[PDB]
Amino acid sequence: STSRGEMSLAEVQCHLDKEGASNLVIDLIMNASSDRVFHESILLAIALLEGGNTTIQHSFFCRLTEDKKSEKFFKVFYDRMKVA
Amino acid sequence: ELSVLVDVLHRPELLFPENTDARRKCESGGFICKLIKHTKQLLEENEEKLCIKVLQTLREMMTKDR
Amino acid sequence: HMHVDRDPQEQVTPVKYARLWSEIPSEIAIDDYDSSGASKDEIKERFAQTMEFVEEYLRDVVCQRFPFSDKEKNKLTFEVVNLARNLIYFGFYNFSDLLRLTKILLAILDCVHVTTPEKEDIMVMDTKLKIIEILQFILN
Image 1 (cartoon, rainbow over the protein chains, first blue to last red):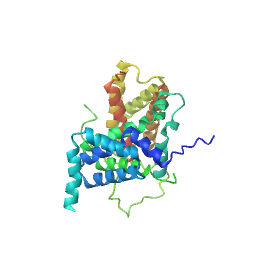
Image 2: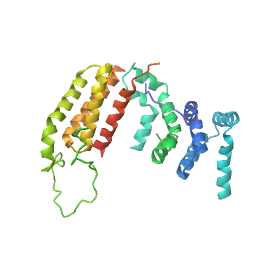
Image 3: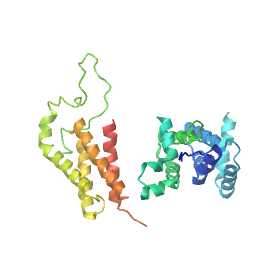
Image 4: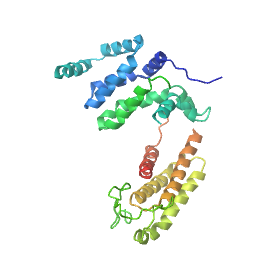
């Protein structure tokens, strides 16, 4: 028929989640060295999580729980807020 | 032009001939997976502009009126 | 290594900025900006046969159905494309010639597309990486 990729916002977010864009953004935040990279990672995560997608929140929680490296992930936010 | 690039990234499997190996690989969504996998290790070699462009395009993939 | 990497040949930039405004730059047709080489031709004519040999060899590789199947021909292809890259970056090619070579390389890759665990040859990937510098130079 029309052969149109309707791809509503929720299914687009879940689709990009399956490949692991969540891991991409969390790792970019983890090993960020420039302000612009961290800012773009934050914006990407905001756009990805918009709408309260439960799958993406579950993926974040699962990786943060299974990964022992999350201490620097929280430190990156803590020191940014402290500097502010 | 940026919108054209994003639209291509939604469905890049159409650019290949049907029933070929490239097209079966791309039809399964492996292109975006490979792209993000390369982007993951990309930050070490100090390519800030290229990683920024990749992230901005991935973010703009989440927009309406496409 | 004997002739190409020798004096007085040296690297040339493809994008210029200190363009003197008082100069001509007339309508200059379309594909004749890369001209007025009154001094480069004296070096050019002796490698003219080499360059046309490179072009005809790449066209022959285009004619071959599978360009990256023979292991022993891969060495010749790799060093030929390396020589072509070094010739280009030293300023030995014109604009139309660069377009012809670009079409040849794209035809090679398109034939590879038509052809399309599995430990591919590392030097095949090296050959594929080699032409990317040529593409960057022609875009500039």
